[PDB]
Amino acid sequence: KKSYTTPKKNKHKRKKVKLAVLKYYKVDENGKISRLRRECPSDECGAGVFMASHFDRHYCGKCCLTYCFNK
Amino acid sequence: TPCGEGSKTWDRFQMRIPKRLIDLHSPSEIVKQITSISIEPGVEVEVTIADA
Amino acid sequence: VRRACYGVLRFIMESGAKGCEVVVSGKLRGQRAKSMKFVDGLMIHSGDPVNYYVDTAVRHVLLRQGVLGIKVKIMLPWDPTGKIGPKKPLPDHVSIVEPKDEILPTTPISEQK
RNA sequence: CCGCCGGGCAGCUUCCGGGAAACCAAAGUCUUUGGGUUCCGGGGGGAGUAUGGUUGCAAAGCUGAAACUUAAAGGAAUUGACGGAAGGGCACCACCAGGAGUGGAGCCUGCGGCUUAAUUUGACUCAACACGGGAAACCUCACCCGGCCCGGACACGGACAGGAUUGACAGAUUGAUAGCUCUUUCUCGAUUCCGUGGGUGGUGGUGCAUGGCCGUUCUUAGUUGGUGGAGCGAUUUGUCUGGUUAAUUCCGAUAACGAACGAGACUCUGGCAUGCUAACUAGUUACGCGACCCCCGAGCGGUCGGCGUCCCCCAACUUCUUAGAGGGACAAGUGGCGUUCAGCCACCCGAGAUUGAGCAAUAACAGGUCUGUGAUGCCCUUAGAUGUCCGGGGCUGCACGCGCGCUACACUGACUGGCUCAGCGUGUGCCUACCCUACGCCGGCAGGCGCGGGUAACCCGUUGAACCCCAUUCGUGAUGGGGAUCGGGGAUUGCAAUUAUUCCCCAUGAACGAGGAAUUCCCAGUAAGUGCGGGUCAUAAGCUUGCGUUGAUUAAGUCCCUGCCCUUUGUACACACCGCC
Ligand SMILES: [Mg+2]
Ligand SMILES: [Mg+2]
Ligand SMILES: [Mg+2]
């Protein structure tokens, strides 16, 4: 038939990052939780919904996985 | 032929469907007697009420 | 194949058939395909007649090797007595009912009733 | 002439008896082994060679090895099968006698090739080539340039929580508002993820691993058994000289008699049925004509010819329409011809014995088909997946080659008025989003925009067609035929037409003035033309399959070519002459 050469750029299958994720939660002295950064406008993602700094991206993850913006 | 080849022979699949119809004037007995009797094989029966 | 299809063919005749046949096409203890055909009695092989008289039946069979075809094709002797066997005659076949009586030339005579 | 007899040349016939068999009064008398005696063979070639001897004037004659190689060579008969053998018979995929073409041009699309990343691909004489229903933008589609997606069943293992990552609204990007991925993180929450085995598909592979289905040898006449009879027995007759027949179909001769499958009979179909049963989902018919009715027309007026309607109907009926039961047509009569049988031929009455398909045996064939099949053997492949797709692309590409089509070449015709005759279908409202269309306006037209009937014999729809038919131009000019190739617009289908989608409107305006070598098609409502349906369809056909319509010429026989059947025969062929050598 042919036998596939492939231009030597074997594309990455990627991990979605490891991440413990939930350590960064400011417990100021007694039990109370609220940090500030950027926010999403969705309903299931109600006010707590939380954002970022990447090489750009930022995303919100709380209408289960329904609804990540474009920034 | 399934698939291509051989000298081109086709079949000529036919089904007929003759319609008879019979007008009448009766009550709701003579209709419900005459229709329910004389059924059985592959026969479809319609029953129009009146005129249209 | 052998002992089985006889067991069938034996049966279907003994049951009460005008005739019958069985075909077991397909590979049969060899890399090559054979085709086997054990036949018995009478069988018409053309006409409209065929359509309401023979009882054709194809069935595959999927085996630990590959695939054979069965074809059973029985001939119905409802020609003798369906009850009113459809048409009954194979159209070739005419049954002339015989003189039965036709006795006596004799001298004339008469009678009264 | 008629006999006999010896010894000669010969013949037929036979269960002597022989004989592998063919055959043989003798090849008889042979495992029941020997009457006398002469010669001579021991697988085939090498080889009747080498060498030796001898004879010969010599050709040569006579005598006459081996190494080596070799598995059969051979003989008799059997079926085959092929003869540039023979009789018989037959097919318009054969010819004759023709027409139509075809093969020439342009165009269409079928293949070949080249080219091309890609022009996936099956199909290779016939029985591959508008064929795979194969008219493809996207799907199709598999294939390439990419690129996404996972739909990894299942189990077996691994993962309780500082939540296994189920599933993520603005940007980097990317094609994509693909969290498919590079931080952020906010939820479903026992799913998840990672191994292992194992699948699961695959329009992957293999049709010489198969089922079915198909194609065909081949709508050709053939094939088979029971009993007899023949052969030790494979086998053979029955199963055939001849006449016949579309047809081992029949009769008869007849060691065969009577049977079975194919043919035939059958089914569907197609035509005669003022014969029947009927029919507002036919027609209706003609009425009765009761009318409207306008001079629609005739006619002063009575009266009439006539479309339309006013119908309805409680007319009447089946004249055509429809579809049920029926009948008939059956070489049935007569005259030839004929073995005076089987039939054939002519004529009568009348459809003269044949209107046309489907069904189609034994037995075949690496025919074709794995890409019609959730039929599938095995093989591959199996996540980066040949799993399924999105986007695009290709399947359409072009110096050449062939294959089926259409349109022409014109004036028995071209375009310009007009008249006017169907049939088989088909249609909505359908398995997942979708028709058939009547009648209003608008627009030239494509079309557009209005509105109406339609499980239909009602609505489309007296299906209002083309040829055809009739009314004017034209004048034999590559012209007004022809009508390709491009310029430009405008509609429509489609989310999208670039790769002119399809259509219209303009505009350009080609070769072809009858086709070189070949070769298929067929006999009666036949060829041809001619539209029209159906199928293919969102869009849509130059494709087929049906349907009428207009409708010819000519064969009505022969085997002259090609190819088929039987019989006899020959055959070193049995991968069957496309052989063997
Ligand atoms: Mg001897
Ligand atoms: Mg001896
Ligand atoms: Mg020897």
Image (tube, rainbow, N blue to C red):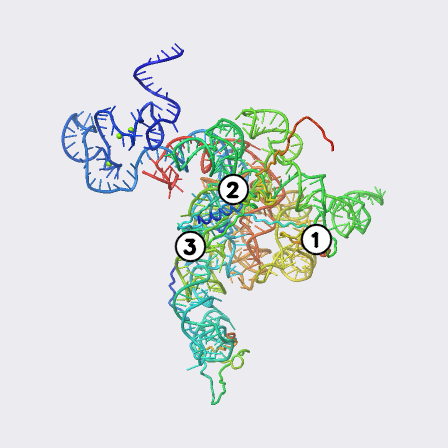
Please state the horizontal and vertical placement of residue D276, each as a whole percent of the image: 72, 42
Q: Assign a secondary structure to mark 1.
A: helix
Q: Residues within 10 Å of mark 3 (few under 14, many from 20)?
A: few
For residue C42, the mark is 2
**Regarding ligand 1, which quadrant of the image does it lie in?**
top left
Find the distance from the CA under tag 1 to the CA under tag 3.
59 Å
Q: Quadrant of the N terminus of chain A?
A: bottom left
Q: Quadrant of residue D336?
A: top right
Q: Residue flagged by tag 3: what amino acid is it? A: Gln
Q: Residue flagged by tag 1: what amino acid is it? A: Ile
Say whether marks 1 and 3 touch (CB < 8 Å). no
Say whether marks 2 and 3 touch (CB < 8 Å). no
For residue C65, the mark is 3
Q: Is residue C67 above or below residue C113?
A: below
Same subunit: marks 2 and 3: yes
Please state the horizontal and vertical placement of residue D183, each as a whole percent of the image: 44, 79
Q: Is residue D28 above or below residue D400?
A: above
Find the distance from the CA under tag 2 to the CA under tag 3.
34 Å
Q: Assign a secondary structure to mark 3.
A: loop
**Pointer 2 or 3: first along the chain:** 2
Going by the image, does D280 lie left or right of D66?
A: right
For residue C86, the mark is none
Q: Chain of mark 1?
A: B
Q: To which residue does mark 1 refer? A: B34
Q: Assign a secondary structure to mark 2.
A: loop
Q: Quadrant of residue D330?
A: top right
Please state the horizontal and vertical placement of residue D536, each as a whole percent of the image: 55, 54
Residue situated in front as seen by the camera: D460 or D46: D46
Find the distance from the CA under tag 1 to the CA under tag 2.
45 Å
Please state the horizontal and vertical placement of residue D150, each as a whole percent of the image: 47, 68
Which of pointers 2 and 3 indicates the residue nearer the eye?
Answer: 2
Q: Chain of mark 2?
A: C
